[PDB]
Length: 237
Length: 237
Ligand SMILES: OC[C@H]1O[C@@H](O)[C@H](O)[C@@H](O)[C@@H]1O
Ligand SMILES: OC[C@H]1O[C@@H](O)[C@H](O)[C@@H](O)[C@@H]1O
Ligand SMILES: OC[C@H]1O[C@@H](O)[C@H](O)[C@@H](O)[C@@H]1O
Ligand SMILES: OC[C@H]1O[C@@H](O)[C@H](O)[C@@H](O)[C@@H]1O
Image (cartoon, rainbow over all chains, first blue to last red; front, side, top):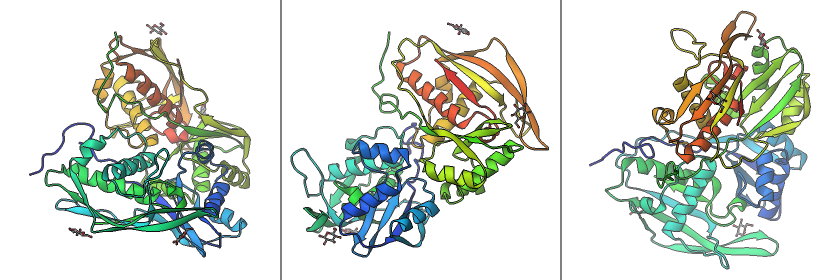
């Protein structure tokens, strides 16, 4: 059975993350150069500049990097005409029209058994004196809730421990992959599929909240160098 | 004596509201025309367009309207060079550099007895049976809480009644004032100074939250037609 929460913290729905994705055509040798280009066109957005000088995560990420171009995802409310005009000045052309995320409304999640997470680019988590290229459930829940809170400030502090009591992670197998960040830096992380299974006791409000955390992580990326395109995930329900 | 909260919803600080203010020189006849100009220069920001279509509160407000110009406050992260260039195209000159709110850090509030709230433009609250140009404490608290949640979207549902247990409002006197919105609509609202006094039982965490609510209300405006410049408030501690 379902028991619905009456309190102020989990008795109300939380906002669904929103973002914009812009596709860019043009050759750059490394993700380092794509990231630098995006900082350059956002020089008059104070929040971006402050984050960069504080070496905090920027409100955007490079995605789908290759030799022909890349995508930019951002949760800032951007004037897209200005983005196109500034990229064109720098020799880059935007392709198609901006994509506004989320694209579709969600159905009710009653009877949703779990969520599939595909790590599409190599992923690793950073720690003092060593990044860890391995999947840890609690570490991943901390990452995705931090990404949700960056997009949606003002959320109360969720307890990681209490979320984990209602979920189980499994993986048939994960594999390794290499991601070249700069001429001199290549990192080896994990890739592949993890299944997030809800326990039968999962409060119904928590399924939707977990989906929204995963949507935020799909926007921001997971783990180290997420703004460079590491830790890119696809979610399936 | 102070008793500190251990629970997750009031035991952690919430974000301070941030905004940008841009001052514009240029005559337009009515606040209506200023509002229209701002919508026009934000035509490629999907969030603003969608909110305008749904008749939701925009994420900006006209302030300081006079014969020779006005100001725009917004809590969007704006590329301010683009805003200046688009205004200049319409014949408006931006004065000086953008102002980033808040300008200063706050001190500890343990000694703070209350807050002075000055209604600098006419203020009124709207209802189906007609606008009410009168100060009501609970209505004001609901207004400022909603403003804070519009700037800081994840903010949980606070109890208005619980907040009101800890504050007292007073005024020496309040005055009336007229605010012309269009060539065919002028509204009469109240103006003047209200004092918000914290009771001695006020939990420490709540003084800072209330100040943040008032800072959000200073950015957004209070009551009807806030985006047109009505209900502008100035806070002093
Ligand atoms: O990829 C989705 C599938 O992954 C499997 O590991 C699970 O057992 C299935 O329940 C799920 O539908
Ligand atoms: O620079 C990023 C690139 O690093 C290479 O090692 C990978 O094979 C590519 O998939 C990736 O796009
Ligand atoms: O401490 C001074 C304050 O005391 C209150 O009782 C008054 O209502 C306020 O107007 C005054 O600013
Ligand atoms: O249009 C707005 C104007 O309305 C007039 O009625 C007020 O006296 C002015 O203070 C205000 O600037």
